[PDB]
Image: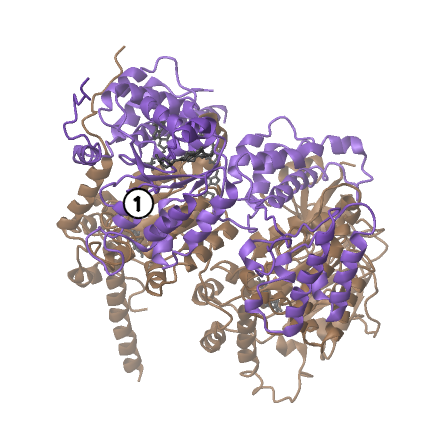
Chain colours: A brown, B purple
Amino acid sequence: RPNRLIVDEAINEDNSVVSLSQPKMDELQLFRGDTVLLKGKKRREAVCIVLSDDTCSDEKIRMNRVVRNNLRVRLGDVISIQPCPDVKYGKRIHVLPIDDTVEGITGNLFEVYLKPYFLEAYRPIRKGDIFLVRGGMRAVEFKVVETDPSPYCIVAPDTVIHCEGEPIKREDEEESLNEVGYDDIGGCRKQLAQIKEMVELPLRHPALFKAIGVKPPRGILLYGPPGTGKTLIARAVANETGAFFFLINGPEIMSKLAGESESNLRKAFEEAEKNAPAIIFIDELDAIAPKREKTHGEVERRIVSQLLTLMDGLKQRAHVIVMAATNRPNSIDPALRRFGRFDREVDIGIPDATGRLEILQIHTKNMKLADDVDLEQVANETHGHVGADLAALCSEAALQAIRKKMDLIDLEDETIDAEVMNSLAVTMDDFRWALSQSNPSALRETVVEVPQVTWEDIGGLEDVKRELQELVQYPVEHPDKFLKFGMTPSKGVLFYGPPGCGKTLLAKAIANECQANFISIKGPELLTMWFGESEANVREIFDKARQAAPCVLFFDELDSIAKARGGNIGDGGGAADRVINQILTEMDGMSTKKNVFIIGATNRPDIIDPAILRPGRLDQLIYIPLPDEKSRVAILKANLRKSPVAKDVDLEFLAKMTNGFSGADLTEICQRACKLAIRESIESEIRRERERQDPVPEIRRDHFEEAMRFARRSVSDNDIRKYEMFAQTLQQSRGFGSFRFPS
Amino acid sequence: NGPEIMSKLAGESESNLRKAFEEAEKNAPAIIFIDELDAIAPKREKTHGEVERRIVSQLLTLMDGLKQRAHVIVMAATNRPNSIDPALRRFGRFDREVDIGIPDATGRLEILQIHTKNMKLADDVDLEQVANETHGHVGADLAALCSEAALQAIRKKMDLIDLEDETIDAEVMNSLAVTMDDFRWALSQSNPSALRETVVEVPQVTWEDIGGLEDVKRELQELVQYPVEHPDKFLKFGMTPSKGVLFYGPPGCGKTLLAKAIANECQANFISIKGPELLTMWFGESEANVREIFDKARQAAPCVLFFDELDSIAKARGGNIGDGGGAADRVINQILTEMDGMSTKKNVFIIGATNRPDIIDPAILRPGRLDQLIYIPLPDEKSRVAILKANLRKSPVAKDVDLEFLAKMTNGFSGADLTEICQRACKLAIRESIESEIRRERERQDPVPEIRRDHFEEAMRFARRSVSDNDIRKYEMFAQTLQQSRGFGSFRFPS
Ligand SMILES: CN1CCC(NC(=O)OCC#Cc2c(F)cc(OCc3nnc(S[C@H]4C=CCCC4)n3-c3cccnc3)cc2F)CC1
Ligand SMILES: CN1CCC(NC(=O)OCC#Cc2c(F)cc(OCc3nnc(S[C@H]4C=CCCC4)n3-c3cccnc3)cc2F)CC1
Ligand SMILES: Nc1ncnc2c1ncn2[C@@H]1O[C@H](COP(=O)(O)OP(=O)(O)O)[C@@H](O)[C@H]1O
Ligand SMILES: Nc1ncnc2c1ncn2[C@@H]1O[C@H](COP(=O)(O)OP(=O)(O)O)[C@@H](O)[C@H]1O
Ligand SMILES: Nc1ncnc2c1ncn2[C@@H]1O[C@H](COP(=O)(O)OP(=O)(O)O)[C@@H](O)[C@H]1O
């Protein structure tokens, strides 16, 4: 039937709202705000309000867990839409707390949860349907029980809502909504999409491999630092097939004396498959099956080497998936990751500045987060916090709001009523304290990110941005033309230009335009590998890129080692280096990998191994010049955009003065102006406090006059001419001007 | 198959292993595959338990018992040979090792063609393109890829047919045209985490891709191909032909291409050890890795080793001072030590390429080692025409490009520089073609199907001679140092 679509992940946390592709709406005979009735796979029906997001395809309709398992429809299945509303808003509608969600809760939970969720929204309700409302640090779901016999009803002023109490819990047909799903993972939407695409076919349709000859993914190996959310992701995926997955987590297996483990492990495989498709999560495979190279007892060696043989047995059929988990892949015995034994590794990795924001929003979603929580600010403030840490933080703050409210309410247990738990407005002061307490001791390792900088933050460089758009973006949006001519485009760039001029910013902005996984390897990170004589770590770095593709590597200060030598003498690399040589060795390898882009930035382009400028390696050198007057205007505007500035600052003059400022120097002028602005503003707020014992709400033209006096050109003209000299060495003309193939 | 044997508690394995030998021979000739012998019989040097030592050392005694008769074969398997206890590879105990090795650019194409053979591979699958695209994919990965593509064609068709199992009919499975877009996605997903190690290959380059060098190709045909197709004449005179060459010549002039083409003409297993690969061994103070490299050649024969930038270490020293090798080096010295050993191996040919022939251990030019120095000169005008034609052969070029003039300009371009001119012409061609396809898209909101004489006019303006005349004369000076004449001109044994 054409009145059907496929359910997909929600765009918003609110329930009762369903997104439809705007082109699909009219053909579906639905309009901008109509009531979208829904008929699920089972003999189960519900209703929602229409919405639209242009990212939705005509195939997809977005429904979150509150609506999906209300139709008993797993994610990715067919939902039928049957619009036919009545005009009779519900009368005497009713609901109960017949659920385990209200364990220990006291007070009039009806007043705090149900009444605002109903009257503030005036949303459509249908009897028999479970609905989740979050607040008071609890997610409480109730099963409607009366709506009048109408197929749908909308709560309104004449809807005299009702409530009653009973002890009966949810039915077997109802999903345990207190446990995770797809919407409970925020930091790794890319890897989550990879995993769900990778295992939607075996698990949703295990027969769909049973019959055809393709061999399904028999083993997935999630990995990433502990607390990254690996077990969360596996549990979220398995909550579509949670018949027997849960009992089969295997971190305890390795620790039962001798064969008691080997027996247990067997049973773990034996019982997981016994009913429905099932996921067998080998939690902390790093411990059960470590590299045999570093074992000192045959009993543990036999444990690991009969993990493999129980793995191989599952190659016969598709309904079972062995989703392992580990801190890093090279800590496990390579006897795994064979064809059929954990064939597909997946790096969950630490969340980025926007992944942590999504994690914080996911965890806070049941807390009354107040009206001053700058989530975006803490998300950048909490760099390095791996996954579960943002979960601890979101509790450390919440508790900081309880322990500072539990003095007012002197109760000895939370038989304190839910209404005052709803009053726990967890202000940003509490989160400020919690961050000060929180420690990112899970890990802080080379971080792969989708940087949030964009062209509007790269003032000037009008030519270079075009020259990089036609270099990173043309070969990935018209590869037909690159095959038609056999070009083999350049998988490399070297930004040579004065330091502090916008090379790293350009690389981040490029990675952002393509929405690619930027991986910055700063100067100290390379120089440390050279110092420790541990150039082998480079093999790890590039490997991360090989896993993070589509990536944009970036070796900031790629000439760091050559500068830290002088480039003239040394037993070692002469002109070359340990780590630069390893970088060449790995660039040659990754020249195959079409997805990853490699960028380097050299503020000393003459002093650097010329072997890196060879074709295939960072071949396309791009000059990043000192900004000219107009580009200096652009840079000043870019840096002042994020700060309040009086409406009479003459920036076109502030650019004229800066005869040759690098971009960093103009940023430093902006920062000196800000510092002098807080000086002049603090020294008038404290003056006001003394008076009582917004002076200036913005920086002004006055403050720049003392901000500029601390200014430089961070590159002498003897360096500007050094880069011009390197350009003319690498501009490569030799009097072919006016050359023409004669007619 | 015996991968499970090592993991059954104590004697339960030792009994099982015996039964494995006992029952394999019971009917007809039978192969006994000791899967992952790396694990069952590791080097006893790195064991910490007597029971595992006894497992490995009663693998040997069950091996020996099979020397009595021929019908049973014990085909072991291992990641690498030196990880197994040398108690194996004795006479009669795994006497014959065989390196399957990673597939080459045409091996991977054959693997892909084998695995795709049941998939409706559509009409736009550039198998040859993915075969080069998928470098480093070891065997079964191309099998996973060939599934990742196929599934990418199912999961994008299973929306149309909303069935819950493949009781979907075979007819619409035949309609799963796995387009090259699906394989493009699958390659982006696929990871060659099996291994990426020094790759032995039969290169697909040939003479037609080596523009010019008409003299050098003959001089190498009579040097690598005469001693292997007329060895009667080399024994008849007792010549002991040269198992070595050093290509000294300006960098980026066609030395590695010549070596690959030579290996291809003989259909030999080329093994390139690039400059960074030697320089890495010298940095890590792990010259012992060279013993591995040459060993690969000893297993991959008929081979053509190739030490690109054989003077890499000397350049990375300056060749004047150092505690270390003075004029010599760690890794160059190890290379000499192994060249002396491999001078026995008749099948393998050893080639080196030096763009800095003066700064390199002269001990490597000794007879038996890379003795026959061959000069790889900068292309002359006709050879530049040849190089330009060779590089533009694979790309569409308008039928009015005046290549015999584009050669005249490039008074001293190396081969790499002319290839860079070709690549700049291509880059400006996509620029001018993309900027008219997007223009067409804006119009509706094949401009030029080929590069043209127009684009080379902006492609050439970014050109070099990558060697100054002070380097051309440096190589001429090294040649006259190694041309070795001293006025025996007109010398004649008088009648
Ligand atoms: C003249 N002689 C003739 C014969 C022979 N020539 C031939 O016949 O070969 C044909 C080809 C090709 C081709 C390509 F080489 C790259 C492509 O695009 C992939 C891509 N995907 N993402 C990226 S980067 C991007 C990913 C997003 C996040 C950041 C980075 N790239 C990409 C981009 C830039 C450079 N490299 C790869 C497509 C092709 F079709 C040799 C020369
Ligand atoms: C003047 N005093 C008199 C007495 C004494 N002299 C004497 O009596 O010795 C006689 C001899 C010989 C001989 C030989 F020395 C090499 C041969 O061919 C093997 C071969 N097979 N493949 C190759 S390379 C090719 C394999 C294909 C893939 C790539 C590489 N080669 C080969 C080719 C070039 C150089 N070396 C070996 C045959 C012979 F008969 C000492 C001097
Ligand atoms: N990417 C993420 N998105 C949402 N929650 C996360 C994420 N990563 C970690 N968490 C939080 O961490 C906890 C899961 O930790 P767990 O998976 O048990 O440890 P590990 O990740 O090491 O297996 C959950 O409470 C979850 O809310
Ligand atoms: N072109 C530019 N436009 C705007 N800001 C710039 C520009 N170039 C540099 N900056 C400023 O300099 C800093 C980044 O310097 P960076 O580009 O990393 O220098 P380098 O790459 O030479 O180390 C940022 O704070 C940014 O505000
Ligand atoms: N004689 C030649 N004929 C055709 N192409 C050549 C020639 N010499 C070099 N090239 C080009 O140069 C590249 C190979 O350079 P290479 O021979 O490896 O230089 P080097 O051996 O000095 O490193 C190829 O892209 C090839 O197109």
Q: Chain of mark 1?
A: B
- In the figure, is residue B19 to the left or right of B298? right
Asked if the beta carbon under badge 1 is closer than 8 A to the nearest atom of ligand 2, the reply is no
Is residue B374 among the parts visible in the rendering?
yes
Q: Is residue B250 above or below residue A676?
A: above
Q: Classify mark 1: residues with Cα within 10 Å, few (<14), some (14-19) or many (20+).
A: many
Would residue A160 be visible to someone looking at this image?
Answer: no
Which residue occupies the foreground of this view, A701 or A493?
A: A493
Residue behind mark 1: B364
Q: Is residue B437 above or below residue B292?
A: above
Question: Which residue: 64% across, 56% down?
Answer: B36
Question: Residue A358 location in percent, x, y?
Answer: 54, 60
* Residue A165 or residue A488, whichever sits in front: A488
Q: Quadrant of residue B52?
A: bottom right
Task: Name the spot of residue A298 as percent of width and height, x first.
Answer: 65, 72
**Could you tell me which residue is drawn at 47 percent across and 25 percent down?**
A484
Residue at the extreme front of the image, as rendered: B495
